[PDB]
Length: 219
Length: 210
Length: 145
Image (tube, rainbow over all chains, first blue to last red; front, side):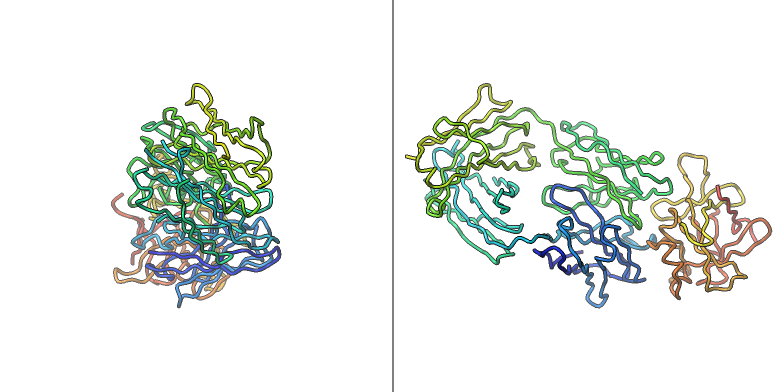
């Protein structure tokens, strides 16, 4: 069973965004689809629900009339149409599923058993901006026989970025006074390995379609 | 409808017994579900229908009701249990609890402290970022101070702290000191001063621009 | 559960046992044991069916999930569904299989499923409520409290 969200991104105050939730492994007829959102550092908030079978829909008070949930049973795909966006709508948006019928096999008390990994939505007059990537080089000052190396991903907007390495310290991005984010990613590596292997981080910032490869070389 | 969760946060040692309480504002509701949320992950369903264990969830999780008070119970806390837990009223206006942060309580561990000069690329760009790195320590509270040429700095740095690790249950801290290239080029010794419960005296890692 | 002709209720059988639910399954049990707290039931009329048959909707959990009769191989089947009783008040063809005819036999009542006519709510002989085709096992009583 798989739920995939798409359509998140940056959007100005008062603008419109449409989200998508593409379902597999279960039928729309036997389930309900839900949108749930979570602002950075905050708790879960339900947004909206739709029953594809019966076509009933429900909405949290804070989005009624701005948001509209719908479904296309032919595509097993649910949609969130968001209008008149405000900054406080900034959040990660998950879609999730529940089994409608108490007699269905995998019934679970109408709890949300499957969720997607979520799509980030930023409401802001600020403009998109790709990141700068600088290496954090190992040296004597970073060894204890383990060495630390990494990538400083600086000055981007909006979130998110993905850093990939081909002993991981995943720091959260920080918001800088410039209104831009920067994160650092660190990896711990044995000192046997320098010279034997060069280390590269892949920084992927989809909003600006940035994709860079910087090598982290000693000293 | 409301779901009041308590406590907002707790720390407990491996193997201890943990309970979290969620109180519903109406008494006709009894289909409470409990979710576990790990750093950067979607919530994961633990308990449904107040007390039924979901397929796959470890047997050390259980849930119970007493009136309008719903309780999640972790019988022997494991390190992988670090998470935020939410309760949920499942119907119609769906309602979550404010959530409970569960930190694992381990022995004090000191930080390994490392430092990284700025890269050349950034210097040609007009700015210098010095990073100081505190690895695999506990507890989370730590003081990190910058001293450029033995002059304590303020305002021009930011700190990032990982989530508690799910295996050894420690934290890591990054401190980025951001300067202009000109300011960077005028001074020689960049020091990072770390004070932590695991260090008998404060530790300092340093490098000279030369 | 605040609508026209909208009232709260507890549903008992001839022997003072109360409808309750465990993981979506409608059961009968002693209201007084700490094991079986009774379903607080919203009752709403279905204004589009024949009023002389007293058509009603049955909403457990204060009206958040409603009882339905579904036609399957094993026969008609009781099912609790993620449908709010106010959505049923909107009406339509689809609300018929959530509709029960409230047929009076004196001071008690029978509950017959509109989508499965001739079939009645049926209490278990052994200690799950079901559907069946006058008996004390099909007799029910409504108390507001």
